[PDB]
Length: 339
Ligand SMILES: N=C(N)N[C@H]1Cc2ccccc2[C@@H]1NC(=O)C(=O)Nc1ccc(Cl)c(F)c1
Ligand SMILES: *[C@@H]1O[C@H](CO)[C@@H](O)[C@H](O)[C@H]1NC(C)=O
Ligand SMILES: *[C@@H]1O[C@H](CO)[C@@H](O)[C@H](O)[C@H]1NC(C)=O
Ligand SMILES: *[C@@H]1O[C@H](CO)[C@@H](O)[C@H](O)[C@H]1NC(C)=O
Ligand SMILES: *[C@@H]1O[C@H](CO)[C@@H](O)[C@H](O)[C@H]1NC(C)=O
Ligand SMILES: *[C@@H]1O[C@H](CO)[C@@H](O)[C@H](O)[C@H]1NC(C)=O
Ligand SMILES: *[C@@H]1O[C@H](CO)[C@@H](O)[C@H](O)[C@H]1NC(C)=O
Ligand SMILES: *[C@@H]1O[C@H](CO)[C@@H](O)[C@H](O)[C@H]1NC(C)=O
Ligand SMILES: *[C@@H]1O[C@H](CO)[C@@H](O)[C@H](O)[C@H]1NC(C)=O
Ligand SMILES: *[C@@H]1O[C@H](CO)[C@@H](O)[C@H](O)[C@H]1NC(C)=O
Ligand SMILES: *[C@@H]1O[C@H](CO)[C@@H](O)[C@H](O)[C@H]1NC(C)=O
Ligand SMILES: *[C@@H]1O[C@H](CO)[C@@H](O)[C@H](O)[C@H]1NC(C)=O
Image 1 (tube, rainbow, N blue to C red):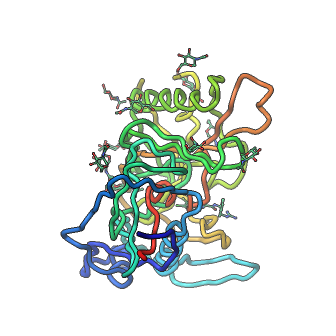
Image 2: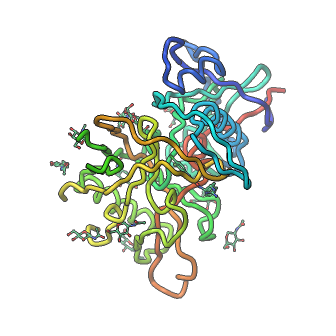
Image 3: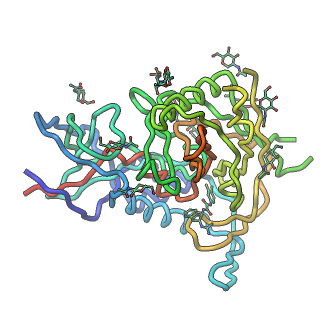
């Protein structure tokens, strides 16, 4: 028997000690080796409640990634709280690796295996494990990249769907590749992402159909972000250490609800830090072909308020609270203390 509890987790990974890549280096010093023979016990006739929106595992993962980025990605200039901090900003090797979150003695992680579990409420198929799956700490806005897919139907997750101020996590059940490149040989900050339009519009149509199930069959309309920092109004992510900002206007096209969709992107040196601490300025992009091919596995949306009088609901890509990114991966886990 057990009870819900918070405690300090540890991390495990297959990081390489000879690698200079920054996630590898961090994990080599902050994590332990993985278990080659992990035990997972199905709990017969046990129903457990989960709440992904109140899960201290998320805060702990956030603390880790902040620590990793603070040690590994210091900028040439940092503008924070009115002060100016200057330091060396060498180019790095950057490519996220899976990190497992694990409980210490006397604790265990319960895992919800209900395929269509929305993240809050009872779960009928529960197992216990010592560690989560390997979660890559991919920082992005608008689109969730390289995450885990929903096993059955597309899932809409929100702390409170009725409250337009709460971000919606759309959990996709089928990956759509996004292929971003800053071509080798001109404007060195100019880039672009390519997406199969036939595949993407198929998925967006399905997302629309799911949203209709939640919003009483009202007409579902997508619109560009209405304002805010560039990190939010654009799909931002890090590719090989460089900060990409991509215009997603073409991705959320109501008309298509079949060719190649090419989003215009730019590598930015000056950034609003997701840690919420201010601005960071980095050096110009490395030479050559900068390329990242990722799976879109989720979408972060915000719904327009005040459309209750209408027959429409309007959605705009969003994000910016990176805790939501971790939430999208940790939603099926909770820590309990064994009594
Ligand atoms: N901007 C704030 N004042 N505060 C932060 C913190 C915060 C908290 C809740 C909601 C929004 C925000 C803002 N978001 C961002 O700035 C941000 O996501 N940046 C960013 C940078 C780089 C990469 Cl690769 C990236 F994906 C993202
Ligand atoms: C319970 O979840 C486990 C792990 O996904 C799965 O193997 C098993 O088939 C599930 N049981 C049912 C009845 O769905
Ligand atoms: C998730 O499921 C719970 C319990 O079944 C329900 O109260 C809640 O409205 C659901 N939320 C969403 C976003 O479907
Ligand atoms: C991309 O998603 C596919 C499934 O569509 C998966 O086979 C592959 O491992 C994923 N690559 C990642 C997560 O880097
Ligand atoms: C993805 O989920 C949708 C419902 O949201 C469903 O119609 C579709 O069959 C699913 N696709 C796969 C590959 O299971
Ligand atoms: C969800 O949001 C709606 C709209 O703001 C609000 O009326 C309701 O109280 C919220 N529910 C909870 C449980 O906070
Ligand atoms: C990614 O896009 C580039 C074009 O910029 C192309 O040369 C490359 O083959 C693409 N990669 C994949 C895996 O589609
Ligand atoms: C709701 O929308 C669906 C499309 O998924 C449609 O088949 C159905 O007729 C609609 N239901 C009502 C009651 O309007
Ligand atoms: C995205 O591209 C569209 C179409 O060119 C443009 O109107 C819009 O201003 C762009 N968004 C931003 C924030 O640059
Ligand atoms: C929406 O897609 C259609 C495809 O024919 C295109 O003509 C239109 O310009 C698109 N609108 C955008 C990208 O905002
Ligand atoms: C998109 O995928 C389809 C198969 O579903 C394929 O026929 C087509 O060539 C692809 N188009 C692009 C633009 O990648
Ligand atoms: C997603 O994973 C692929 C394959 O490991 C990697 O090449 C790509 O850069 C990743 N995307 C991001 C944004 O980390």
